[PDB]
Image (cartoon, rainbow, N blue to C red):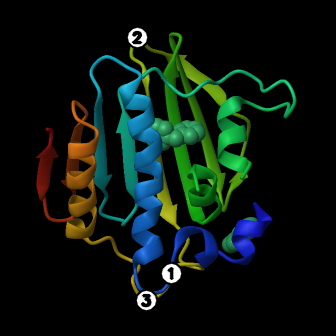
Amino acid sequence: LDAVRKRPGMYIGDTDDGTGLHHMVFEVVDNAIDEALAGHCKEIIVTIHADNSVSVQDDGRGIPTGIHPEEGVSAAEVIMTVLVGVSVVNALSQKLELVIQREGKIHRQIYEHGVPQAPLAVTGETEKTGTMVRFWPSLETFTNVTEFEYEILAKRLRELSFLNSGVSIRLRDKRDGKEDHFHY
Ligand SMILES: Oc1ccc(Oc2ccccc2)cc1
Ligand SMILES: Nc1nc2ccccc2[nH]1
């Protein structure tokens, strides 16, 4: 991921005017919509947390967790660490936490600046399926505009709900309680 770290704006967009900051969310949402479309209930939830991290979750099948035969690490870690996709978001997040519910197990992993802190690990049992990512944009990269703007996210999620009919998209702001539900 060092090519991304060297020139973040070439991958995510302008890192000073808020463009790249909000594109971080959109790249994660792209992956969440993919996952939601492959499951039964087809809902994603985008949450702006009070510490200006964002989480994105889906109720799909779960990102695959088995060891990648050539890379020698979990498939999830391959997606997160091989190069626009969520690997760029990971590289530019001072922290990124993920949870995958799949085949009866809960799997968790934490990254800092794209670096895995331990291998993907089973932490418990579950009867649910789906994926969640919460990320803290790196304040070493994103300057000036560092806080998420609710309406910038809402405008894009609204567009996506028309294009991805039948996918339910909820947006929640824990800073001021504002919420929306886009479903076409
Ligand atoms: O709801 C989501 C959020 C992020 C997603 O992308 C991922 C990529 C690799 C591992 C985990 C997640 C997939 C689904
Ligand atoms: N603070 C900080 N910034 C980093 C960038 C790349 C890898 C590790 C890092 N720790």
Distance from the alpha carbon under mark 2 to that under mark 3: 43 Å
Q: Which of 127/159 is in front? A: 159
Q: Nearer the viewer, mark 1 or mark 3?
A: 1
Q: How crowded is mark 3: few (under 14 residues within 10 Å), some or many (20 or more)?
A: few
Secondary structure at numbered mark 3: loop
Q: Which amino acid does label 3 sit on?
A: Asn
Could you say which quadrant of the image residue 48 lies in?
Answer: bottom left
Q: Are marks 1 and 3 in contact (CB under 8 Å)?
A: no
Which mark is on residue 127? Answer: 2
Identify which residue is drawn at 26% across, 69% down.
Answer: 152
Viewport quadrant of the N terminus: bottom right
Q: How many marks?
A: 3
Q: What residue type is labelled 1?
A: Asp
Q: Earlier in the sequence, mark 1 or mark 3?
A: 1
Secondary structure at numbered mark 2: loop
Q: Earlier in the sequence, mark 2 or mark 3?
A: 2
Distance from the alpha carbon under mark 1 to that under mark 3: 11 Å
Q: Residues within 10 Å of mark 2 (few under 14, many from 20)?
A: few
- Residue under circle 3? 144
- Residue under circle 1? 14
Identify which residue is drawn at 61% across, 46% down.
Answer: 110
Identify which residue is drawn at 51% across, 34% down.
Answer: 99
Secondary structure at numbered mark 1: loop
Q: Which of marks 1 and 2 is in front?
A: 1
Identify which residue is drawn at 61% across, 68% down.
Answer: 11
Q: Are marks 1 and 2 in contact (CB under 8 Å)?
A: no
Could you say which quadrant of the image residue 77 lies in?
Answer: top right
